[PDB]
Amino acid sequence: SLSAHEIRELFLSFFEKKGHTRVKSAPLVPENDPTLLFVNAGMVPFKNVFLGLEKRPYKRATSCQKCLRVSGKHNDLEQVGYTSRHHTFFEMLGNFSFGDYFKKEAIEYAWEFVTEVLKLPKEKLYVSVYKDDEEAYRIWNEHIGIPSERIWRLGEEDNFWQMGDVGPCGPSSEIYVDRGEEYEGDERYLEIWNLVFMQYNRDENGVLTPLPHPNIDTGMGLERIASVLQGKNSNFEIDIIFPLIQFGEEVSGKKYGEKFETDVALRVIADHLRAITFAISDGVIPSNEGRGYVIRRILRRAMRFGYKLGIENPFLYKGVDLVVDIMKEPYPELELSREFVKGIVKGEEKRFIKTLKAGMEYIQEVIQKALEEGRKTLSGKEVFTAYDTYGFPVDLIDEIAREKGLGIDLEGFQCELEEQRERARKHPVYSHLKELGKTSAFVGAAAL
View 1 (cartoon, rainbow, N blue to C red):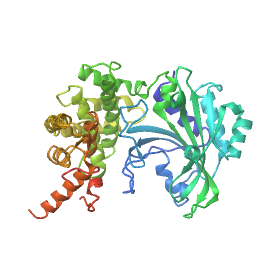
View 2 (view 1 turned 90 degrees about the vertical axis):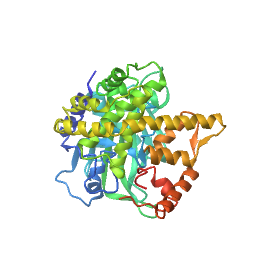
View 3 (view 1 turned 60 degrees about the vertical axis):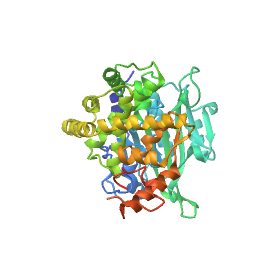
View 4 (view 1 turned 120 degrees about the vertical axis):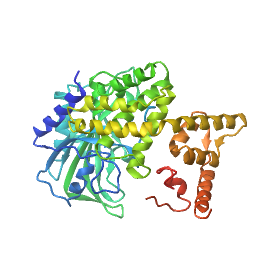
């Protein structure tokens, strides 16, 4: 029923066929973009080209991009593990137009690949349009032949894309597949492709102007679409990620499908193995600031859940070899960094397990001391201690405390943060005062 690897090739080849130029995936860390620590979408590297600043030999491009949404206005690390759709790392299959073909062509190639390449039924397919997108609806309903009953006219928060506050923007059309009456909602009508029509110029004023040369930018998550073709009810059960779940089962001696909590840890470990492998492979080294901290919190999270499963010895390092052997066909460079990634990961692990263990005992203790004493949160001191003494990331402490119904004293943490500061300066990272509380969720205690 089509393997992940197959779908990726079919997409790329299909578009080269449509004159698009296969563009190698940019690395996860933007070369000269101290702005974004991680490429989140296929378009990111083409940004300046859609802007018209940068030049490209071609007007049509297609690619499968290495993506990371553990960050910013596109940061799902928080949900990772709890749902069957969220990930840190993922692949975006996309086709782009640089002032060349637009709406119709965008819609035709999309409709042909879904119906004639992926082989999905034209009857279980739905498309959404910008409510006042007369052009889009018309082409969907008249040119393609989509029965009006299968087309939804939605608002701005649903089909109006924007690059930023001021910026090229425009309508978007999403193709959804109806997976059956045994499902419902955004799970039954699973969106698998979002086509973006950059038609307007949003002045600073918020005033929109047509673009002289409109552009096309599409995005289809690979795992999600593979899950549809392979008849799965989760992205973690697809050919390219299920073995990672199994990885967890074997090392834990626990099984997948028995209890939520366990499935949560298993999914966390699997999603984070891919994230850390592709991240370190692309140059990111664990540390306490920026990218290094993003990955460090990731590896930190996997370790903690792995221990939650009862795993007492380093293990994430063994998963690395699995990730590489699985994604080596589309990402051969991984075999060259396989042994380097494995070492960095084992170093972190061997370099972090014991502290996480003692930290977990400490944290649990105070939690239990809290709910026994009627407390409904962890003190600023209790947070700082596990943050500064056991090295726990601010978010990791919150998640742990969260499982018990307890939260953490946000203001008291901040107060404690200043104290240490005024303390350290009496008795690189660069924070603002009263923003120490915010920064800290992004750096290590040693950093502040």
